[PDB]
Image (spheres, coloured by chain):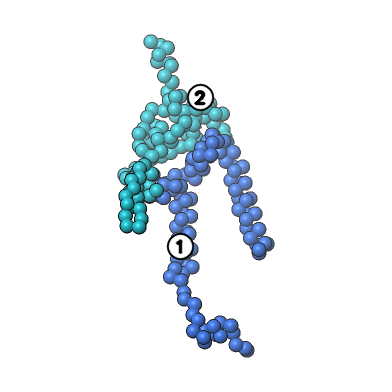
Amino acid sequence: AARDLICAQKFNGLTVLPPLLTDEMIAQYTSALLAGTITSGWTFGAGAALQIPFAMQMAYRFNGIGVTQNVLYENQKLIANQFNSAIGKIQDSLSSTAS
Amino acid sequence: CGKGYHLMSFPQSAPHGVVFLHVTYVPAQEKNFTTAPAICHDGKAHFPREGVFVSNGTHWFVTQRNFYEPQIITTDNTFVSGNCDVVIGIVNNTVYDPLQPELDS
Ligand SMILES: *[C@@H]1O[C@H](CO)[C@@H](O)[C@H](O)[C@H]1NC(C)=O
Ligand SMILES: *[C@@H]1O[C@H](CO)[C@@H](O)[C@H](O)[C@H]1NC(C)=O
């Protein structure tokens, strides 16, 4: 077709170098962080990962912010539904809005 | 301030800089236990004040989260909120009352 801008850049001594970590390794690190956060909580950031059920981890998170932990154990289905709806809204806003 | 749970820090001077010695707390040796969110007793749900319910297979205890120090489950270290029909994963156990043996003596 016609000459590209990238070829004009490369023919005058300007080169783009590749990063050391590929996107597969960045996604692997992100997946490891997500798996540790989902299963263990904050225990994997201070040493060995210690398993806990996610409901009890979320009750710990509720006690952190000043709400008593029986609120989660009495509204667990509502809290899970609200989280799922918020994740779906993040999905829809990323599918529609491009700015 | 370092990796782990932070306790202390000590400064030292260096050529064009500073060196921090961070003293932190790391958990070391772990064990598996069976855990529950609440305890059903007398038609009531008991939740721990601070700590977590654990079981070694036979008996149920309450302990602090960052160190294994099991204790007898008592109304002093638990609070009551509602009945057992709304909590998912509630178990059946007895809750000790210190007033009852003092009343009989
Ligand atoms: C706990 O259970 C898991 C799965 O059965 C096992 O791999 C692990 O060795 C056990 N002990 C500790 C201290 O995590
Ligand atoms: C706990 O005891 C009640 C009766 O007091 C019984 O209906 C219920 O099934 C028991 N829970 C379990 C898990 O066996």
**Distance from the alpha carbon under mark 1 to that under mark 2:** 49 Å
As drawn, the chain in blue is: A
Q: Colour of chain B?
A: cyan
Q: Secondary structure at mark 1?
A: helix
Q: Quadrant of the C terminus of chain A?
A: bottom right
Q: Quadrant of the N terminus of chain A?
A: bottom right
Quadrant for residue A8, please give it.
Answer: bottom right
Q: Amino acid at mark 2?
A: Asp
Q: Which residue is mark 2?
A: B42
Q: Examine the rendered structure and indicate whether residue B80 appears above or below residue B98.
A: below
Q: Give left or right: position of A74 versus B69.
A: right
Q: Which percent across, then down, holds residue B66?
A: 38, 39
Chain to which mark 1 belongs: A
Observer able to see residue A55: no
Residue drawn at (48%, 50%) of the image: A38
Q: Which percent across, then down, holds residue A84?
A: 60, 50
Residue drawn at (38%, 47%) of the image: B4
Q: Amino acid at mark 1?
A: Gln
Residue drawn at (46%, 71%) of the image: A19
Observer able to see residue B16: yes
Q: Give left or right: position of B69 versus B89.
A: left
